[PDB]
Amino acid sequence: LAIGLLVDDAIVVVENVERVMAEEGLPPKEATRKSMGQIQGALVGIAMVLSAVFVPMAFFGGSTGAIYRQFSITIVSAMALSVLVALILTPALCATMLKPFFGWFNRMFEKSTHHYTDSVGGILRSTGRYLVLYLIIV
Amino acid sequence: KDLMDKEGKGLIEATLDAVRMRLRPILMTSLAFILGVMPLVISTGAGSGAQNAVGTGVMGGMVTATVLAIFFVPVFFVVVRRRF
Amino acid sequence: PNFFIDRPIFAWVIAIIIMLAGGLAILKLPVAQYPTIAPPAVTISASY
Amino acid sequence: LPTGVGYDWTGMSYQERLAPSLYAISLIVVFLCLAALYESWSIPF
Image (cartoon, rainbow over all chains, first blue to last red; front, side, top):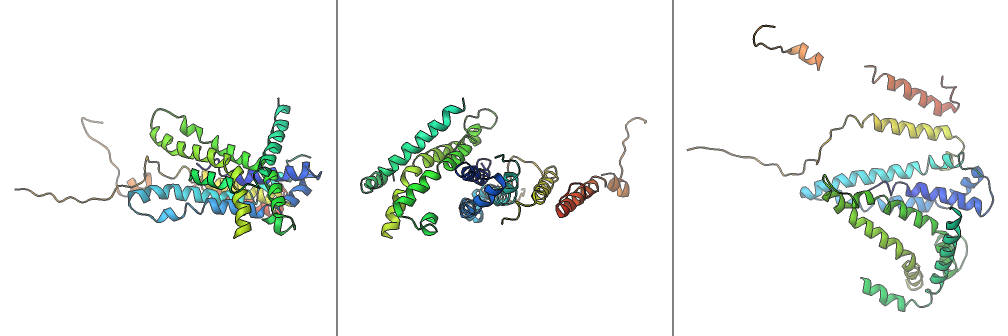
């Protein structure tokens, strides 16, 4: 339950580097150094918020608490190690390896990235109508 | 918030700009999770009640929290930052 | 912070060290289905 | 071996029965410790 949560930070730093180099035109080594200043808060938050809800249950009681601690130790240590790795090793790999049917995806994604931005634009004017809808869900 | 503070931009303008630039990471980190718990959900045989019980909840929770957050969080970001 | 982008070796060493400290202790820990989660008990047997 | 008798070691014999494994891992970690210090992958040698 941590394999799809330990790569988050690593996947975030790698996406930024390539997004800061493809939309700008900088060399990998000079790109990472630029991207690492923009998301330290993001990566320094995900690990914190994700491993902070698993600490309070380590102090419960009964057989249920004994079951809880097994998840607690594992997920919390995984998040701490994930933070280090994606903030100590990830950069290096990015500044060394990252070089300076697939066609039908990028455009598709771009079209969906645009249509979604337009829909969000068409939603930030009628917050009252989107407030009752949310209430129903609760 | 960072883009507003250390960029001197408008509320809605920065909201749209951030939600546009932060969509590849959200989808990537969401599919890298939802696709990692199917081995627990579709499992069967030899102690598979535990795996199904563990994985089925988080699979649905991630699907919903990734298809509704991108549409709702700008709403109660702008309204909250506007009304306190 | 931005100090592991100039010397990759340092980062590689840290990664291997941690990997070597995990595999060395991966064959020393016990294996069980569950931890100890049942409440302990005590029994008093008599006769007549 | 006669009819039905057994063997059993005790004291020092039972203890000792029940080195390089922890010595080969100490020579590999010092090379990595040195490698990080010098950054050459040959300087450590």
